[PDB]
Image (tube, rainbow over all chains, first blue to last red; front, side, top):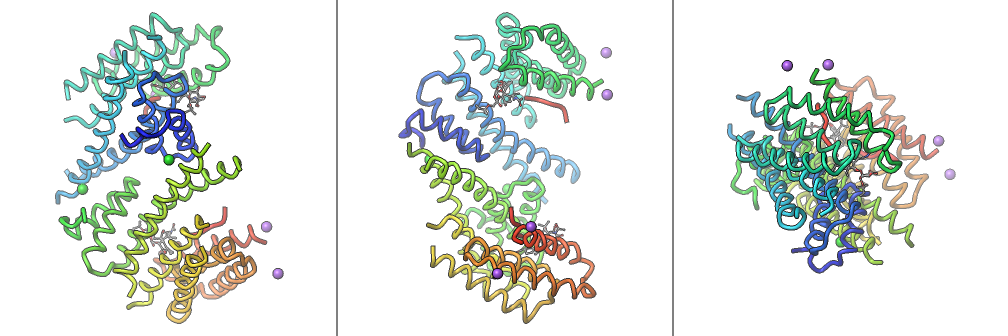
Length: 224
Length: 224
Length: 5
Length: 5
Ligand SMILES: C=CC(C)(C)OC[C@H]1O[C@H](O[C@@H]2C3=C([C@H](C)CNC(C)=O)C[C@H](O)[C@]3(C)/C=C3/[C@@H](COC)CC[C@H]3[C@@H](C)[C@H]2O)[C@H](O)[C@@H](O)[C@@H]1O
Ligand SMILES: C=CC(C)(C)OC[C@H]1O[C@H](O[C@@H]2C3=C([C@H](C)CNC(C)=O)C[C@H](O)[C@]3(C)/C=C3/[C@@H](COC)CC[C@H]3[C@@H](C)[C@H]2O)[C@H](O)[C@@H](O)[C@@H]1O
Ligand SMILES: [Cl-]
Ligand SMILES: [Cl-]
Ligand code: NA
Ligand code: NA
Ligand code: NA
Ligand code: NA
């Protein structure tokens, strides 16, 4: 690809520069180039990859929701045409990320496996947000479910990756799978079991875990 | 171009949709397509064009400043390489806008002429921000100066376009032409003469004019 | 809007 | 940062 001629270390370096500059499309391209080098990603490098594509698709999703809302309000073809254009671009990015996960990253340490399986569920979920669909939802559920099984066996309840996986799998249940009670149960059980495990909250993971715990409580407050 | 097959009215419609979705690159492409249809832009259509490219280059400039600051802090080649990459992209957008102005829009009513001449100065100024340059600065000065002459003869002191032109020409003096006193004099004279002309502030231009007057006072407070 | 991470 | 419009 376009990044084939650049050193892996230089791609990682420029991904951090792009992050500081809030150039997330560049950031994602650099990290894709790094994945293409064929070596496994470190903990920090996985974070760079996830943050880059999370922000890229985040902007596309937000734009899609604005256009879809306008489209539904109208019950010419321009609104549909432009919404489909943003939708196609969004799907393309999701396909790019899913391709990286399945071709390179998903294979190992439970921390990395759960990380990538959460991503797989997330980007199938984003595909499901715009799908008009059952296959996509099933693929998201499988990834989330496998990640849940591993994290339950291999990771403590306060681990931020385990917490974030549960937060998103709960959101999946609520607004994708039309299972509000399952979403609520999962969020509550996750929050409660993490609250009883704070004695093992490890200095460099305290801020991430407590942040996600508050996001879990945010959703419970919204849904109950 | 890519927009050649789309109706002019549809391009304008999708530019407004893109604005609501904060998809400014799409917005700019749609408005470029509209300009390419060969007809003059209405007052509202000129605003759509300016807002689209202002936001596109605004993000590029902000990213460029982050990277340039990092580059100067370091006094490997990665930082310079990535800064040059963002810089080249920024220059390309400026060249695209300048090409539209010179090939299509600048030719008419004083309101449109001043509008486009301000844009020409603005995008030469953005080129000057990254130039390492005298030709570029001279081109920005000419455009601003011609716009100033027209606006002084044809427009009231409270006209938002005249006010915005003076605000930006003042910024040009301060940080591009290294003439702080000229920047200060222009900002003060502009503010003062608009304050004595509020009796002619016309309902649908009051908010724009008072906003820009506050930006003029913001800069004077910063510079004095 | 509900939270994800 | 100084203002422009
Ligand atoms: C590489 C450098 C940068 C600056 C990009 O690192 C970003 C942040 O990466 C770490 O954190 C991660 C994390 C977030 C925390 C909730 C942010 N924390 C606070 C206080 O806001 C939000 C991110 O999207 C990310 C990567 C994603 C996942 C998701 C990833 O699913 C695939 C699961 C939860 C969470 C984990 C992995 C957090 O470990 C560090 O620990 C933080 O210091 C650091 O800010
Ligand atoms: C087409 C629809 C949209 C929503 C995009 O229109 C945007 C705004 O276009 C009008 O305003 C203009 C204006 C601004 C005002 C300062 C915003 N006003 C407030 C209260 O924030 C900031 C913009 O960049 C713009 C276009 C640029 C120029 C610059 C343009 O140099 C080339 C000069 C000053 C100013 C003038 C033209 C203002 O007339 C309307 O009057 C406002 O209602 C409307 O929001
Ligand atoms: Cl379209
Ligand atoms: Cl580069
Ligand atoms: Na119930
Ligand atoms: Na509630
Ligand atoms: Na002096
Ligand atoms: Na001061």
